[PDB]
């Protein structure tokens, strides 16, 4: 079960994208958002976003969400369970800043429309999508 | 927009897996399930499953669900919206049966624990993510 | 069945597209990722759009033995493709294989003087299936 | 360029499979082999295999090979360049042993047909396969 967490945090860190849905917001649609973490494992999970993001208005002090995640080869599927709330902490913005994130804000770190969400993940259901090689066959083409 | 649907139905048909969550069931966890459709496009979307699946008990005449889907290289993400209900129709079982599905049932098509769900999808929000290859860099390895 | 195998291969190839293609004595034998295209749903030849200044071109002469390395996205299939590779910048073929994606690569469009087309005449491939089965789901404290 | 190596070693470590071809052996066919490394980065790269593997007979003191690698998900392609030779070192077998490797040998670590190859990689050409997320569009179906 330590293996599982490791695989998850690795997949998550490199593949990043989490589809994130909130009931009663936008018809419950799960939006693809790019996850970021400090370090190689362990949350919270951070998403850069925009102040006008509808999700923001409705999060209040924090809300229960289910994040849907798959690795980019579908060898791992995780249903992430945790609390989601805005936490646009300037210190955190500095830590998580990079040229990729930077491309999104006209105003840079100081963009008044910049927002940051944190997902405090307490558990995830994780499915491994494990494979077996077979004798390779020589075939005329 | 015709194109987006085509891309979607294609990814869905070959990649298959959809993560499917129901609130008030199992803490809202989205379970990976394998989608099947007749023909190359158009729903409904069918999932083989088990009678004891908790989701079943709670579907009643049908329920609103959001299916989360990505293609196998993440060049497409779809949030699928529709109604989900059991419809273990013997005719449908025959149409959708194959060796892969067969591996799951001790009893075959006749397994008393076999169940089939249909998702009647009315819309999906679809995000394209297409990759373009950067230029190759030589790199030394220690 | 060995007909199954070819079908899976041609399908993976058609949708996944990328083939890593190496030539000895060219560029240190490095296998470059190139995007394969075929007419129809199966069967070669396999076509790669490329550039006239591509070093590979200089060295192909009337045609050359190459090994193309291919995996499907998700890696459920690996194919080692064996065939002859040669330039065949046939205007008719360019028209048949043209699309907005290919178009994005040429400043001059179909008329770009630096446009080149390669054909790989594949006679056989060694093919390995790697199919994946989903394990029971585990819940982890996090 | 440090980023690139990191991504490579990570993809390699978790995805493992490298297609490995030798001229004048088996028509130059690149066989899918599962790479293993000690630690999270840095070679050599190890492949468990069999003594009767034709590749073995022809490696002598070592040979130049090109290993073709992609990540599942095709966000990274690496052409790996290095020297390949058998080095069935008992200490190394112990270090790299696991239930997955174990499933391949009737005789376990002691299987007389067990062989281990090491690829001493000096460089790789690496291509990143970079994506652009477009704006989501609702569609009818």
Image: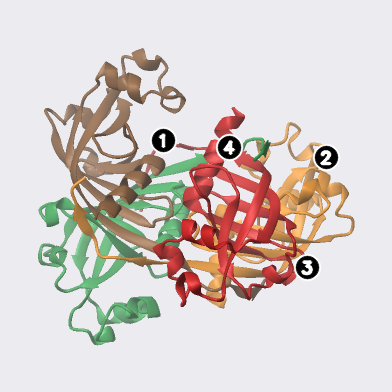
Chain colours: A green, B brown, C red, D orange
Q: Choose between A92 and D13: the one closer to the eye.
A: D13
- Which residue lies at the image location 40% right of the left edge and 20% below the top edge? B105
Label 4 environment density (alpha carbons within 10 Å; few <14, some 14–19, many ≥20): some
Label 3 environment density (alpha carbons within 10 Å; few <14, some 14–19, many ≥20): few
Q: Position of residue D70 (x, y in %)?
A: 57, 57
Report the disc number at residue D52: 2
- Which residue lies at the image location 70% right of the left edge and 50% below the top edge? C83
Q: In which quarter of the image is the C terminus of chain B?
A: bottom right
Distance in Å between CA atoms under marks 3 and 1 = 49 Å
Do dots 2 and 3 share one subunit? no
What residue would you read off at disc 1? C136
Is A84 left, or right, of C105 in this rendering? left
Report the disc number at residue C25: 3
Q: Quadrant of residue A141?
A: top right
Query: Is residue D32 among what the camera can see?
Result: no
Q: Is disc 2 placed on a helix, strand or loop?
A: loop
Q: In which quarter of the image is residue C55?
A: bottom right
Distance in Å between CA atoms under marks 1 and 2 = 37 Å
Distance in Å between CA atoms under marks 4 and 1 = 31 Å
- Which residue lies at the image location 21% right of the left edge and 58% below the top edge? D137
Distance in Å between CA atoms under marks 4 and 3 = 31 Å
- Which residue lies at the image location 62% right of the left edge and 36% below the top edge? A134
Distance in Å between CA atoms under marks 2 and 3 = 29 Å
The chain to which mark 3 is attached is: C
Do dots 3 and 1 share one subunit? yes
Report the disc number at residue C6: 4
């Amino acid at each position: 079960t330590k293996e599982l967490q490791e695989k998850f945090w690795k997949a998550l860190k490199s593949d990043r994208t989490v589809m994130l849905g909130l009931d009663g917001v936008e018809d419950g649609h799960a939006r693809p958002m790019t996850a970021q973490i400090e370090g190689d494992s362990g949350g919270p999970i951070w998403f850069f976003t925009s102040k006008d993001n509808a999700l923001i208005a409705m999060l209040g002090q924090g809300r229960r969400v289910i994040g849907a995640f798959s690795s980019k080869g579908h060898d791992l599927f995780a249903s992430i369970s945790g609390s989601l709330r805005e936490d646009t902490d300037p210190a955190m913005v500095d830590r998580l800043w990079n040229p990729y994130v930077a491309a999104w804000y006209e105003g840079g770190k100081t963009d008044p429309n910049l927002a940051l969400l944190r997902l405090d993940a307490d558990h995830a259901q994780i499915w491994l999508n494990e494979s077996s090689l077979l004798a390779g066959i020589k075939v005329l083409l």
